[PDB]
Image (cartoon, rainbow, N blue to C red; front, side, top):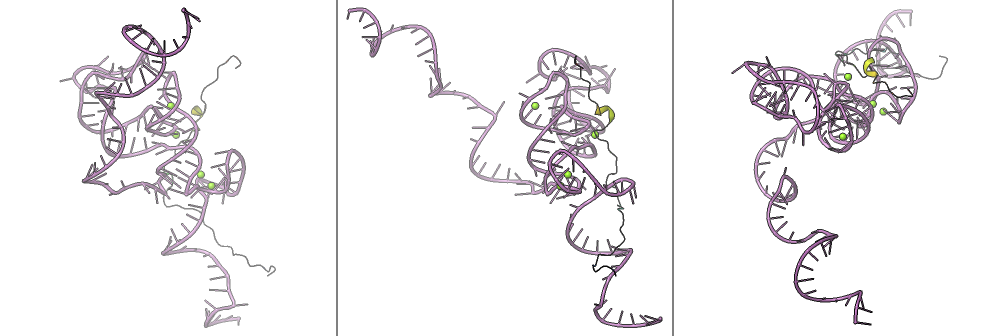
Amino acid sequence: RTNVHFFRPKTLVHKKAPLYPRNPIKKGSWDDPCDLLRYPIKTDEN
RNA sequence: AACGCCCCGCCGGCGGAUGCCUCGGCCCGGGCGGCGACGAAGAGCGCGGCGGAGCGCGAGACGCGGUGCGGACCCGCCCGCCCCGAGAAGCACCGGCCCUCGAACGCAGCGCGCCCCGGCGCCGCCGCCUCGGUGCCCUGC
Ligand SMILES: [Mg+2]
Ligand SMILES: [Mg+2]
Ligand SMILES: [Mg+2]
Ligand SMILES: [Mg+2]
């Protein structure tokens, strides 16, 4: 023992493994490419 | 004087009483007694062919689908429907979609992380896995 300090030991850590899915159906969002673009702007400067 | 001011007989203003009318209030009785981590109540911001407030709805947005009933309209301009079903207005139930904050849950409030595969809040109960103790013992050494 080269250190005078008691530290919590190291124990095995597991990963998540749910019994049932939290999001059974994959759903879309706002980020579809065609809906992302709205419309062009039309002016003489443009 | 005459004008001005103040008092009768007609006509005009200004104002809004009165009378009549009201899809509104107030009281009494009866029923009901049903919200939420499967994300509530509340807030913000968006959504209409021409669209400000209110209602409604949520990037599937002024609504989508199913099953029954209904049977000619759709407040403006348009578009649509028209028929022994071919289907406008309406009504009931059922299935889904459901942006940001909020008990509000990776941190923070509009910015930024960890992670290796996708996901990452707290407290409790039960169960399991991996461990600590000069606690009570035991064995071997
Ligand atoms: Mg969507
Ligand atoms: Mg409005
Ligand atoms: Mg949040
Ligand atoms: Mg927070």
